Length: 403
Ligand SMILES: Nc1nc2c(ncn2[C@@H]2O[C@H](COP(=O)(O)OP(=O)(O)NP(=O)(O)O)[C@@H](O)[C@H]2O)c(=O)[nH]1
Ligand SMILES: [Cl-]
Ligand SMILES: [Mg+2]
Ligand SMILES: [N+]
Image (cartoon, rainbow, N blue to C red; front, side):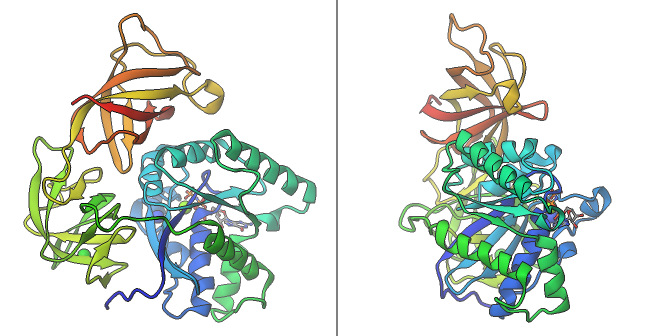
């Protein structure tokens, strides 16, 4: 059908260590919110972890986007994988969030991807975090619960989140989800577990602010994914960063290719509902005429033509992680070629250290230049993560664009 705007729109999502309950919580949110609002369509566990490879491996691999709303706001929710091998997908998901829900298992406490997701969330600009302490149905001991909360708050403090202030909601994603399956009409106040999900919804409503967005600046949408719709054509998905897009607009596909390509937008949808106009903050699919899925990819940006010049060379201020933060034990030299993550973009780059700086060590704050092997939409003040060999090794911010 058609998308009707009645409420402010905010993008949230789920992050946290593997198996702590992100997807189960995402499902419970749709069911719980749907009882109050009939515009919410429910999403089961298997509707979210739907890919054959997810069924095969028993984990989330792809980000999934689901929709729900409260009385206050409309939400698009990006559910990210927790497995260490799918961090790149999680980063692309977090790059779309105005706030993240950090899921931590009460039975396990914070674990290495609890830390890594918090760190990475910051580096793609997630401005606020709410915590859901999950699986409390498995933990009798009140003292362990208090310890887990304390550990999570302190961990958040380590990455410059206000850990002492974030809401920490204690519940069971699974028992809420079970109650909603048995009674899909279960309303607030009727059930203990469902009410914890309402506590989460209230915290999301009130603690994660609606961002200040600019719809007057040139259209810019980082591409998070691309697929072929049988019948329609190639669709590029993403959160619109600024400006607006309408069907009929010419856009440029910028980055990751030798040259920029122009095409015409032939459709705009949010959660499979047609948008008259996509605006900053919307989580959309943009149908692109005359390009295949081999001609658009994650990490490119769609932009008002001529508004963005992609770049390959920049100076950066970089913090290199210590080993206890999951970084490398050893340093690196000029010529080090790790991966750089900017918003939804993942690209290999060459580190070139100043003359006289021959080695950078874990724990170092340092400045150097990077040469990307492919051009990428970049700008001064843009935060990024550095990863190599399947581990996060650094966090940086672009200081100067050289080329
Ligand atoms: N006891 C209990 N088990 C739960 C709860 N929530 C989830 N689980 C169980 O925990 C396991 C993982 O749940 P899942 O939602 O897939 O976690 P995830 O964080 O999405 N995993 P991934 O990191 O791969 O995406 C499942 O076996 C699920 O049934 C809960 O509140 N209580
Ligand atoms: Cl579309
Ligand atoms: Mg999952
Ligand atoms: N998924």
